[PDB]
Image (cartoon, rainbow over all chains, first blue to last red; front, side, top):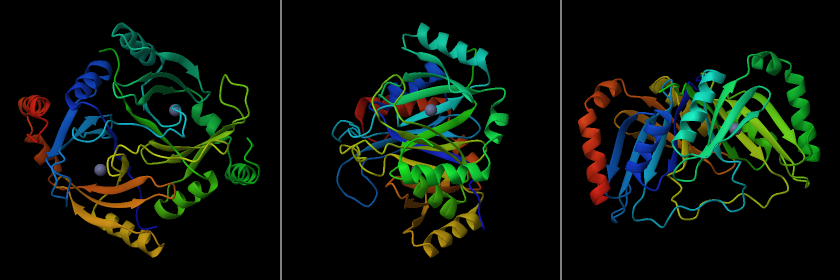
Length: 169
Length: 169
Ligand SMILES: [Zn+2]
Ligand SMILES: [Zn+2]
């Protein structure tokens, strides 16, 4: 291979209101507003169809990005997929940070589920003001040791068995 | 604030076939398979409803994650939102890496759009085997200088004007 992925540059979703979204992510998660692009038409088309594209700081140079499309029909969803599948999780340093976040969100009126033990990490869950599913998580102190038990042979075997049976291997 | 977001921990989407997805991301983008969770029922429910949750290495500890839900109705989409809105972009080091990636993808039969100049970064676009919109990008050498021209006052003003008019400020 002549190239390697460095990191996630940005992950983009639709939002209902750019200013309300910027304000919420700053207030609830201290995520700073980096920049915005905006145009009154979609590239290569003439028709009036404005958008605002916003970048938010998600840490270590990662960006959480939104588009507001004020002349498009209201955002919907993939009705064939459960809500818990599509989500974004952000890492916090440790349990003290996760509990701090949980308390802060609750004090600001956000319903928070958790803490949930996923073995290699521990998480809390809440919705953003656009209905996106968010997760905050910290890695278990023994996470790398538990992951390292998965050998390349086990990975191959698990995928093959799953491909054959579509039951948990 | 008593906590800070460190980075994106994982971003999750649905995939149609776990093994084909793992194989494609390794072949096309050299993204390694880290681990998988699988169960035959969704937590807290009894009914047969298996899933496989896979983590792929997206660089610097970021994870691109997928779920395969083999007993659910086929994946769909939000029909009220254009395809170009929801997407994920991964960073490459520089133009040589982006052109290497473009050539590699094309040699493996992937249609690639680009290179597109976005001023602060340069990008190529292609679909994954699940219909997700992918982007590879490298940052312009003067990107930080161009972004630094946006003062906190300009950000406030742009959001206020946009909130009022819903036209590009
Ligand atoms: Zn998760
Ligand atoms: Zn993009």
